[PDB]
Image (cartoon, rainbow over all chains, first blue to last red; front, side, top):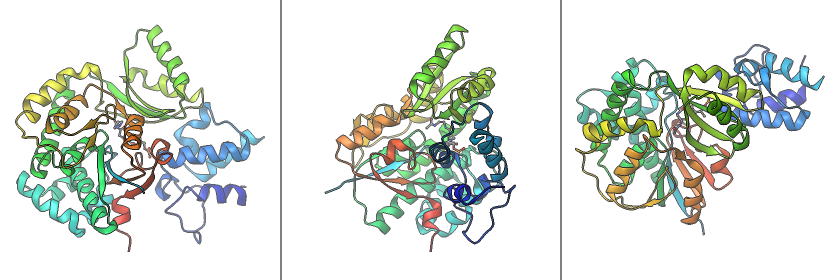
Length: 79
Length: 303
Ligand SMILES: *CC(=O)NCCNC(=O)CCNC(=O)[C@H](O)C(C)(C)COP(*)(=O)O
């Protein structure tokens, strides 16, 4: 259920995923190169773009495990 | 108009599959491995392959080889002439070798000896004490959490100042799950809980045991270029001061902002971070101040 705006944003922080490879709902983000400081930058970009503040459960490791869970988490905050 | 510093990073979690192929093919690593294997009397790459954990003695020695080699690789392939150098945490060890304060052989011996020393100390001392890293934590938010710990009589020390909102806090792991939820409750994000812990006034006995059993036997030379202390950015110029830096590591916090302000004051505009690293080359403290070259195994493996 995500869109181009979200995926273009995420893919800036996934260095081991090529532009011609699909972004699967359940791909492990850490395995395609999301790491601690990539997450800080991602968070800063998601918060500025969507006018949201990630806090409480939205800052657990589980939030950034897959694009599926991260999209759901961002969605619950934008509405 | 610029000037270049060579920086040596802290050790992140080893991952042999990240570097085993690099180490045996790159000529800079192969040359140091020959020396490390002769000093140690075994195959470091073989011992490191079989090591469990992320911070084994073997992964700490291999991390020394990888950082010191990638500093030389960067100098020879990028025409770098650094005026100054600095090492954060483990990188004090790598900068001692690069600067000439220790022969590479004595740096290998020291790295192995300190590995064994810390293992033994933390087998029995400060049981359950851990070093937490976290980000998006402005000092004002951290200070409120420390006051809550104080109110409950819970011992802690700040172990690293990384950036204005990035700290390491050392305390008993019984506080770990509260700290993590308490950080998140104000928009701060916990990263990692390090065992064994590092950089605490309470670790005087580890300093003393390191000094007696590992460091005092060694001959320290004056570095061939100035070294910035990671404790406070002091510009070091003698072997005695490098030796003091390695001992103070146990009992004084990393102050990364003070390394960056000192480098700036010594006229540095560009830094080379030598070795595998996903903190010192990328953190805002560094990138706001300097052009960064990140001399990683991944870069040196590129065609
Ligand atoms: C120099 C010092 O004292 N550092 C703190 C203690 N050392 C560590 O915590 C080592 C592990 N460090 C790392 O995992 C990375 O440095 C991060 C940035 C703490 C987390 O990286 P991530 O991609 O999960």
